[PDB]
Image (cartoon, rainbow, N blue to C red; front, top):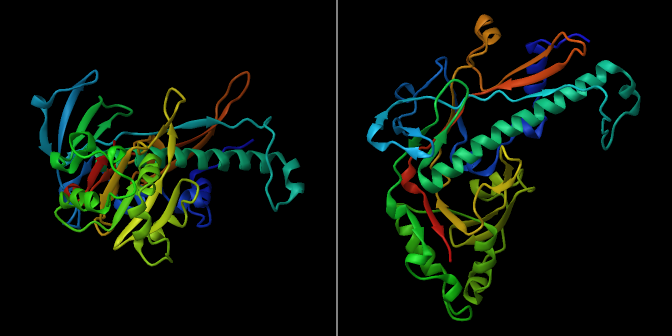
Length: 347
């Protein structure tokens, strides 16, 4: 067994026809679809060619779970959470073959190592994209991210979303308490959308929100199931049918139910978007995922530090020699304008 070099791993990562590589989760796709890779470890927001994205954040240290906001300050230098998940390449695994494919290769041990390597690479990108989506949804819904990673101390980024942009039905009119035969929920949605200061053209909803909205006769009468790749909102969902459902339109407002989940360190399943939350936004309000430099010595040696991802494969010596694949990345979502997001907790 010889370890694949990084050109060999990049050949796969860049291949063009792997969904895990070409698509990203919903909030990332709608609101952070652009990319900037930095040659510095830290993201330097002041250096971006696009003037229309956010160029500073209020960064505060933390002691435990406590944010030390008196020690925070606006800075255009952002330290990203450095990621480098790895997996063992165990050739004793049973390899699942697809689904139109070619039984004969699976004898060849090289072919089998390749299957495990590429399989684990796909899983590592999924995990990096999942962290990014978590960061994206948190930014949009709370204006804040908690950043952790290799070689830094845990701290908070605050994009300072206006307080009026985060709304709870329990401070006003609850949908659960309305007459489902007579209430017009559109007028509440319009009320929430006022807070964006600009038009909202997309409503992204947890499951409980969609259930409730649907229970209103007056929503059903206006609900326009018709659609056809007719909007950026709609286009964004076509490759995310595992976690996202495009429902139609309410006037010029696209309707998306979002049910994406991730697993946390504890190995527990969580929603990206809590089921009782809806987000109003504008699909023209596009920021980016900024990538800090890759800090791996071999990346540094070979001048390959400016990269979204940097995959490595190696075999260690030992009584069992253990083989690993690992992917380095230092992503951070940066919004265009945080003030154009309104989040509502229904009750």
